[PDB]
Amino acid sequence: FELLHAPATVCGPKKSTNLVKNKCVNFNFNGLTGTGVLTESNKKFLPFQ
Amino acid sequence: QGFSALEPLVDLPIGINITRFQTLLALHRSYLTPGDSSSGWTAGAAAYY
Image 1: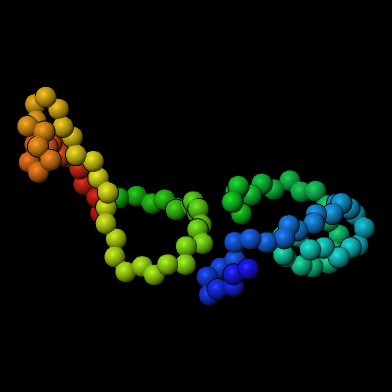
Image 2 (image 1 turned 60 degrees about the vertical axis):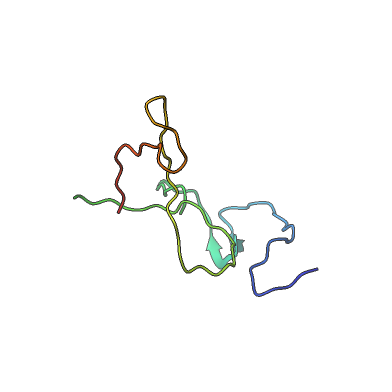
């Protein structure tokens, strides 16, 4: 196993979990963290944002 | 002249050290050219900034 000043390249894998909606919940999306209610939305992002 | 945005294209984990770069470009050859590696070549015209 190699550890270096360079970035990591082999990992995990991570575990995904089921989505839930309208309830007040803790959420952890792609390493972003917060709490709230989730609902669907009309606005469109760009595909890389 | 004019205005436009630049998108993100790709990201690579290449932890190397960089100091210089070189542009890689094609040279044309044909029955019209002598075809010699040193002198029998045609560039057309091209420009970069």
